[PDB]
Image 1 (cartoon, rainbow, N blue to C red):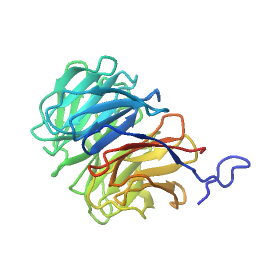
Image 2: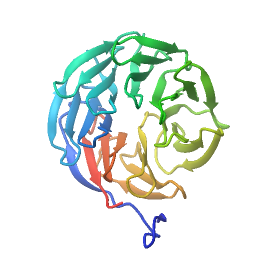
Image 3: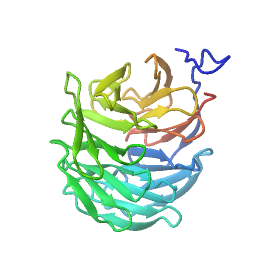
Image 4: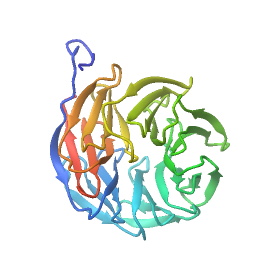
Length: 315
């Protein structure tokens, strides 16, 4: 499965090894993200709480609480100062990380808010809901700027591209959708011949590629500009849950994903080969994240497991 990097690294395979296990959530873990400054890891969970731990030592930092029901997603401001969380209480919350204080509640969705990100400028927040819409919010006012009639089933994931000019969305209706932030227009619908529910989507770090997970045990690399699926990733288990997935780019080029067999899967991006399967979880691995500068994976498992795990690699 070796990958070609530079001279004398013709055969790079990653070697992630579990370093820390992070414990405290009293229910299913839902989302874990590294802060852009790589100093912190935020997690959300069905226990209604968001926790902050050290990205390198995994030591517990704090509890941020306020949501009246469970939490499906969490996202950092571009300066690592603010959090946005998405909840079963139909709202999102904006948090100052230093004080742990709720800055804004974002009210307007009529159902569970499943997913959230800030744009790179971090003046804007996108969210997907069980209400079947995608919403665009002003970070500094709480105003819903736009409601997009995005899909015809709950909205699984949303994300902003490199300059924040586009939003990618996915849903259970079998659709990945690209919207113009400025205009609220649908610019692309991406779909292959089959139409399985779309459990996840994210733009690659340079905006040129999209990574979609579908509930037929598959991840796909799409070229956005062309509507062309380019690479497919299989071998793992994804038929029920909306698992987070990732480009790993600090080392070799990998695709990292949780799987429903309790493993973290990692693949050669180029050749699609499975290069590593990571053990330690005892329930479905629902979320994974990749550290901004170190070869560090954060994993998080479901209700029978309740733990976050941090693995470390040399590439």
